[PDB]
Amino acid sequence: MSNISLIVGLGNPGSEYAQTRHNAGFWFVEQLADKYGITLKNDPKFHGISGRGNIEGHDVRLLLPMTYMNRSGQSVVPFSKFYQIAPEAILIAHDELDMNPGVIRLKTGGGHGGHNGLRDIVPHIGPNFHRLRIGIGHPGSKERVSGHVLGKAPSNEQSLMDGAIDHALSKVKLLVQGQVPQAMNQINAYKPA
Image (cartoon, rainbow, N blue to C red):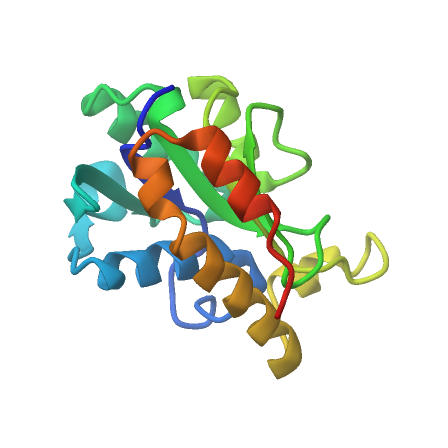
């Protein structure tokens, strides 16, 4: 099993989007970058913000597409092709409607599950990349879904999510060291304290 060498966080650009649930992936990758002192810089060539540096003994690339969510593939696809990074070496963090705040899962393969960022990426690199599904809750009904993902969560729900994110952060060592089964067990076992 492949080392994770590219970690992508999905979200929307702009300060009106930064605290919205749909940017759960950006939160994770931004906090990761600063945890390890990796600088995220404008990378217009790949329509994103990107960095690279040492994470627990490995050279890891970080990517935040700046394309807007539904166009995320225009930044992910050419970036991973250009550096010749196989999907099996990619981790994509994103908000997951189908899990509650404070729930977090690592998953390998599968489709987009309705997620409009993943929808723009599976067609072009296939489904064989890892995903960190950061639960954001489901708002009730289909009509509300959109104002939910594009809205800021209340305090209580934000803490749950931040707790889930702190936990996945403490497992990235296993991911970059190629221990994916072990990461999966330990991420998937998380429940708020």
